[PDB]
């Protein structure tokens, strides 16, 4: 294309970043409409929009919920650019690239944590916080059927895994995140084919809720989650 066409694309991306910056529960409705007006033009523009959204989500995980809703709107309204049958769950360009991108962030954020596996200690603690933010955003997307079962199980597996370095006394926020995910996605993941895997997860959970190394709040949070499953997740 031309140099001006490249400039036009770059100005749109700078605009998308601004919109994401001032995104709030109160402004959502309006800014969401603006984003839809300029961020669905083509495949190329969709790729950048997704890159920026995930960028912001990991910077402010507190708003995962908000950004997840933004992805839902785009998934439903953005036009398809790939080349389905009636009654089949919708499949589009946006949906496909979103799934792909989160798989990418998950791999990079994982590598940042095991980079050491002094000053380096402060670095690891920051990467450990990024990984949790990443997992929380994934949970929120799964809730709206924007990502699949495979990556969710991958999140659960890393949260329950016991590293040699880390000590049982330092897994509070890791275990707290797990209970969050479990209450958010647990019911949809726990179907017949998955009985074996899930049974395995909750056994591991029961043998930790009585640990003297974990705070009171943590082991009470595990007990409440376990009890919910024993009740077939029925309210």
Image: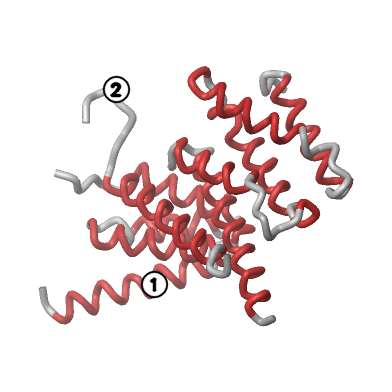
Residue that appears at 11% across and 78% down: 2
Which of the 4 image quadrants contains residue 204? top right
CB under 8 Å between callouts 1 and 2? Answer: no
Q: Residues within 10 Å of mark 2 (few under 14, many from 20)?
A: few
Residue for badge 2? 87
Q: Residue furthest front?
A: 164
Asked which secondary structure carries label 1, the reply is: helix
Residue 140: x and y in percent read: 55, 45
Residue 149: x and y in percent read: 47, 35
Residue that appears at 32% across and 71% down: 12
Where, quadrant-wise, is the N terminus in this rendering? bottom left
- Residue 221 in view here: yes
Asked which secondary structure carries label 2, the reply is: loop
- Residue 20 vs 182, above or below: the answer is below
Which of the 4 image quadrants contains residue 83? top left
**Residue 5 badge:** none
Residue 93: x and y in percent read: 27, 47
Where, quadrant-wise, is the C terminus in this rendering? top right
Q: Indicate left or right for 20 with 1 as reference.
A: right
- Residue 26 in view here: no
Q: CA distance from mark 1 to mark 2?
A: 37 Å
Whichever of callouts 1 and 2 sits on the residue coming sooner in the sequence is 1
- Residue 208 vs 169, above or below: the answer is above
Asked whether 70 or 120 is in front, the reply is: 120
Residue 86: x and y in percent read: 24, 24
Q: Residue furthest left?
A: 1
Count of labels shown? Answer: 2
Residue for badge 1? 15
Residue that appears at 79% across and 32% down: 224
């Amino acid at each position: 294309n031309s140099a001006n066409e490249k400039e036009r694309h770059d100005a749109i991306f700078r605009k998308v970043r601004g919109i994401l910056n001032k995104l709030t529960p109160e402004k959502f409705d309006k800014l969401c409409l603006e984003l839809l007006n300029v961020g669905v033009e083509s495949k190329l523009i969709l790729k950048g929009v997704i890159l920026l959204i995930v960028d912001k989500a990991l910077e402010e995980p507190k708003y995962s919920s908000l950004y997840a809703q933004l992805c839902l709107r785009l998934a439903e309204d953005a036009p398809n650019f790939d080349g389905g049958q009636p009654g089949q769950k919708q499949s589009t360009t946006f949906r496909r690239l979103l799934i792909s991108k989160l798989q990418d962030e998950f791999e990079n954020r994982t590598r940042n944590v095991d980079v050491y596996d002094p000053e380096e200690e402060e670095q690891r603690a920051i990467a450990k916080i990024k990984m949790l933010g990443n997992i929380k955003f994934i949970g929120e997307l799964g809730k709206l059927d924007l990502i699949h079962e495979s990556i969710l199980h991958k999140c659960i597996k890393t949260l329950l895994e016991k590293k040699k370095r880390v000590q049982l006394k330092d897994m509070g926020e890791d275990l707290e995140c797990l209970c969050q995910i479990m209450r958010t996605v647990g019911p949809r993941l726990d179907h017949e084919r998955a009985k074996s895997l899930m049974d395995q997860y909750f056994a591991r959970m029961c043998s930790l809720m009585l640990s003297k190394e974990l705070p009171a709040r943590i082991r009470f949070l595990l007990q409440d989650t376990v009890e919910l499953r024993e009740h077939h997740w029925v309210p």
